[PDB]
Image (tube, coloured by chain):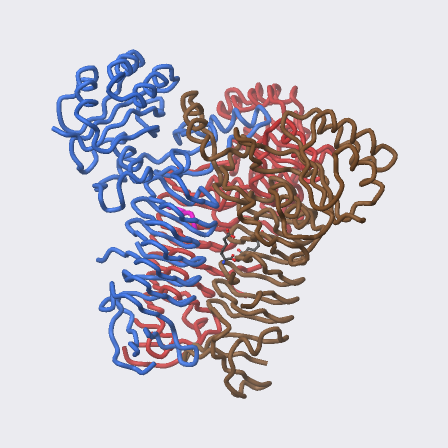
Chain colours: A brown, B blue, C red
């Protein structure tokens, strides 16, 4: 059969041979049967979704097999052959709920390389597969081995920098997609989809399985599962919640410190400082500003050309057209 | 007498021999008289609260004394003997307002190692004892020596990374306690108390003498002096203020971009986007209006829900 | 004529010889004609605003010329002569809209060194002159060369740290002015003016051409073009709007509340209540606490001793005196 994805990885492991993270230089969506046919016998792949650890020798073998079939992947495998760290090939026959750390990391790569979009890939039960880990300037480190490494650094008059303790690394450790700006890279997780023409500013944040079509200006918080359409601006310190999935249309404008608990349609505007939820009672208004009726926000969810605000004289939530 | 605390430190110093910071690998709350008796004569400790700089030779001596008494401390001292940087032993006979940089750092360590909880230790006049400093990837640097170090890095085609200019370093430089998650480590100061099962997210922040019982999900700002009870969630960009001390009960839920200027009881809920202060007039409900009272008078009571009327903008409390 | 500014720079370049950034150890506002007269012939400077790349040999020459005239600059040039990276002298005859990357960086330095204040310098068309770049712990790197560098790091079991993808580096890479505190240095761009006695906390942010007279406590977002007067406090996650109409400024002795926001310039000693966003078109209730009249905030912009709160009971936006 035709595989969903395949990628050759270099990773890091703790003393107990558990995998902490994998790096994939060139992950492949829907690889050709030519590549699979040449690779399967050397790895010992028959079927299904596998994380197959291969040796330095197999690297060279694989590298050789793919000459004539795919040069880029061949070249990569020759570099992988030389490496100091362990190697792993992950072949995914179907888009299915992951079952290894190596598969977990592949899927996150696909998102962030833009090969797929949010919600187009299965991520069920991914948390238990991502081990909590110390992200230091010398790489991934196991939390049980941390203190000792911290002590040796200090005894040499040095410091081991620890920038995150988490189950998700930051994206720019693995990839930086084209035509994008990220002010502070700590605030974008691997799995984020950052679209072409997007600026993610310092106060901006983008979680996994989330992001922007592009172009766009993100100064606020894009939660996991949320996708923002082309041309929309998210103002400083604005929020999206983490039932319904929240999404944001094309050409929208969310104000600074505002927040949305419902999916917005195309060309919507939320006023600065305004938090609107699904159960919020809103005052709907016409061409002139006249009260049509009182509905809840969820009933106006997904609709275009809305303008939400809060009356400065009387504290009423309004929604104009 | 029985000492309050003791710890053996390796630190950094500027050209003028002033101390910028101290690292304590294994700080001790209420150390046994056995340890003290073996250590005091070699250091020259008689009484009170002292920051005693000891030499590489004394390290070995101390190391040897403690064999049979306490192995872990003995082993540590042998490593300390080899070190490149200066050493300091700080012995605290009482829990009292600090009088040296070294003692200042010890107390912060106790908090962050979870040996003590917020408000259970004296931190009066700590600011003037903590010198403002450049925190770089090669360690602590004095601000007056910074530019020169910056210039040499650049001339070699390199960059000296400067991640903070502050009187408090970030916690994970010194310790990372067990069963915790910190998305961005820049946002947790040394002195923070991060309880087991807590996740501090990117937008989360925890100052010194503050933190969480654990478990909990912190996506907001926990100010100095504030302690959050077990099971509570603090939403994205929510605030606690920096009179009354603010605290947060068990099982609470603070909404995104909300804010609390009063202590919340167990199982309280503050709605998203809502800022409630001590002088805020609130509408108490049974959802029939019972009366109108000030938020300070509702302080510390359980099972509340603070929200605002979307039709008329009235602050309520069902 | 008398020059506006001059500075000798060490920078970094990509493979195509385009300049990614410049570092200026000691930039000079209004340098004396003595310094100019000694430097101009060796560099080939006649007139106008020039970015002149000079060689390691010229460095020594320049270094020698300035002995007796200016020791500090002489000393610096002798160190620059030894350097591994390329050198550039930027001489600015007038305060004018920039025309090179090197001039762009010089002007940012002047702000951040405090030699000039926000709005006192021409920054028109600066964006296209600042190339988007990967800021890593080994320096500036071109985005087109990134992936390869990332790969080599990983093959050696290491990690290349990438802390920002942006057209502006963070300030503390170039300077840290005296008597200041910056909790998180990622949140202050080069060009920011941080005044003496200021504390910029973790949630605080200061963009280019922006900042504080000093002293002050900044726990919120100071947008580009915004200047905050002496003694003011900006509370946690508070906002100021962007010019990118009126320029927003903040007076002396003001107090902005946590999560609040200002879309108008505040006068001296103004107070904005926590959680309150006030814009130019916001209808406000002016008070004496008896209602005097109802005006639009823009009519109260730049005036002192106000108190903008929000009535808890009926949500009316008030302004007491
Ligand atoms: N409910 C929120 C916050 C949880 C993120 C924590 C995590 O994924 O580690 C959201 O969906 O963003
Ligand atoms: N709205 C913010 C930042 C705009 C984007 C910054 C940039 O593009 O460099 C301000 O005006 O301060």
Please tell me whether residue A84 is drawn above or below residue C104 in the rendered image: above
- C28 or A45, which is in the foreground? A45
Q: Quadrant of the C terminus of chain C?
A: bottom left
Residue ID at (47%, 61%): C248
Please tell me whether residue C166 is drawn above or below residue A83 in the rendered image: below
Please tell me whether residue A161 is drawn above or below residue A311 in the rendered image: above
- B90 or C92, which is in the foreground? B90
C289 sits left or right of C176 in the view:
left
Q: Quadrant of ligand 2?
A: bottom right
- B163 or C49, which is in the foreground? B163
What stretch of residues is rendered in magenta?
C199-203
Q: Position of residue C89 (x, y in %)?
A: 62, 32
C33 sits left or right of B100 in the view:
right
Image mark count:
0
Q: Please identify the quarter of the rendering in which residue A270 is found.
A: bottom right
Residue C52 visible in the picture: no
Q: Position of residue A132 (x, y in %)?
A: 50, 42
Check if residue C69 falls in the magenta segment: no
Q: Position of residue C245 (x, y in %)?
A: 55, 66
Q: Position of residue C4 (x, y in %)?
A: 56, 40
Q: Quadrant of the N terminus of chain C?
A: top right
Residue A283 visible in the picture: yes
């Amino acid at each position: 059969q035709s595989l969903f994805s395949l990628a050759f990885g270099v990773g890091t492991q703790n003393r107990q041979e558990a995998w902490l993270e994998v790096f994939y230089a060139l992950p492949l969506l829907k690889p050709s049967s030519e590549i699979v046919a040449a690779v399967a016998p050397i790895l010992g792949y028959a079927a299904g979704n596998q994380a197959l650890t291969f040796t330095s020798q197999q690297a060279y073998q694989l590298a050789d097999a793919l000459k004539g079939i795919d040069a880029a992947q061949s070249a990569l495998l020759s570099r992988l052959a030389e490496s100091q760290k362990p190697l792993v090939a992950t072949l995914l026959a179907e888009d299915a709920a992951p079952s290894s750390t190596a598969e977990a990391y592949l899927k996150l790569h696909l998102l962030s390389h833009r090969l797929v979009k949010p919600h187009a890939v299965n991520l069920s039960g991914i948390f238990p597969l991502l081990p909590n880990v110390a992200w230091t300037n010398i790489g991934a480190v196991d939390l049980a081995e941390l203190a000792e490494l911290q002590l040796e650094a200090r005894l040499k008059g040095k410091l081991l920098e620890v920038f995150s303790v988490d189950k998700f690394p930051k994206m720019t450790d693995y990839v930086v997609p084209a035509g994008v700006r990220i002010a502070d890279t700590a605030r974008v997780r691997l799995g984020a989809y950052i679209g072409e023409g997007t600026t993610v500013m310092h106060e901006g944040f983008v979680n996994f399985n989330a992001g922007t079509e592009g172009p766009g200006m993100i100064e606020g918080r894009v939660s996991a599962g949320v996708f923002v359409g082309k041309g929309s601006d998210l103002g400083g310190g604005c929020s999206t919640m983490g039932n319904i999935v929240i999404s944001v249309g094309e050409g929208c404008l969310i104000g600074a410190n505002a927040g949305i608990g419902i999916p917005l349609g195309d060309r919507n505007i939320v006023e600065a400082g305004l938090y609107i939820t699904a159960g919020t009672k809103v005052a709907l208004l016409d061409e002139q500003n006249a009260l049509v009726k009182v509905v809840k926000a969820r009933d106006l969810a997904g609709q275009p050309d809305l303008l939400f605000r809060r009356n400065s004289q009387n504290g009423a939530v309004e929604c104009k057209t």
